[PDB]
Image (cartoon, coloured by chain):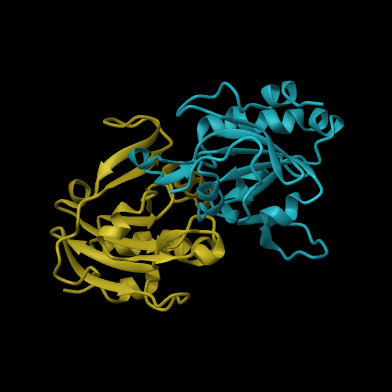
Chain colours: A yellow, B cyan
Amino acid sequence: HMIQVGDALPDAQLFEFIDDAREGCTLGPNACSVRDQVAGKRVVIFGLPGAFTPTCSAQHVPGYVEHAEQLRAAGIDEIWCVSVNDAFVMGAWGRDLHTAGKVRMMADGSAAFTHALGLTQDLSARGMGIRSLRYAMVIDGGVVKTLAVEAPGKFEVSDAASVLATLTS
Amino acid sequence: HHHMIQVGDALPDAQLFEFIDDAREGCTLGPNACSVRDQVAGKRVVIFGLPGAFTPTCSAQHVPGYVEHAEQLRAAGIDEIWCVSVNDAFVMGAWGRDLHTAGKVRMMADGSAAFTHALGLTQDLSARGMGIRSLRYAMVIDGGVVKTLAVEAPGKFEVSDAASVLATLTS
């Protein structure tokens, strides 16, 4: 059953690869709580099917890196890219796409979060197994405020431009 | 789900993908699907499986030992060396380029875990955010059959390294 507007965001454990010395952090993969991490923040989360894949890498992530300044000026606190990939892979992908300080690369490699959101899809035919649908959501007070989920294979609503255009008062 | 493969067993078929970046006949650019049994037919093949692309022991030790030993393994009559992992081909492609595997170790994506499941060689690495992945192992295949099998206890790396495999090739 799919997550909806008005719903509380389900908790799950995600991992983020940390490349630099930071406090309360170790080097490499650091576990975190989705609910703990969105408490008291306004957060855009965009999920996508996989690190290192063409549309994800060429278009979807770069649009958010390029829009980060405008999203933050408009009051977004953090921007997360969530994928069903582990943190080592998300970390390498983040270093390739120069995401540091703009988009948190959030690994859901066990698909726990994507499952709790009801947003998985079966990409076995492509050698990818179970992965996320492509989407963007805006979270405030730990509640889903907007939700844009793409039909399989499409990229019409979850890109950073559409999101910036649909932030609301 | 499946019982663990054993010495003497026929290798099960599965669909794997290898990322191919040069142009070559019969292939396209990027991920190419291929049949396990079709690709081992008439060859002598070392397959080592491991838990994940870009992870530390896999990256620093396990794959480089095979790149390093690839000339000796081929002199001993091995036709191909495959690295199998439960990762998709885009990730395996990028990893292989980072590790200079071209022409030495084929980076064989089992991103749906179909092959690893068919081998009975999966483990649950959820606690570290990796979900279902492969055990670490190495096997030598000849005539479509498992001739030797070395499966690691979880978190161990004492029998699937290239040195051990070279040492245990047989006449």
Looking at this view, name the residue that lies furthest to the right.
B75
Residue B139, compared with residue B61, is above or below; it is below
Relative to B126, B110 lies left or right: right
The picture quadrant where one finds residue B89 is bottom right
Q: Position of residue B32 (x, y in %)?
A: 68, 61
Q: What is the x, y in percent for residue A61?
A: 45, 61
| Residue A64 in picture, x, y percent from top left | 40, 62
Comparing A23 with B94, the one in front is B94
* B135 left or right, relative to B105: left
Q: Residue at x 23, y 61 (%)?
A: A75
* Residue A12 position in % (x across, y down): 24, 49
Q: Is residue A114 left or right of residue B7?
A: left
> Which residue appears at 28% of the width and 65% of the height?
A118
Residue B33 in which image quadrant: bottom right
Quarter of the image containing the N terminus of chain A?
Answer: bottom left
The residue drawn where x is 37% and y is 38% is B128
A149 or B135, nearer to the observer: B135
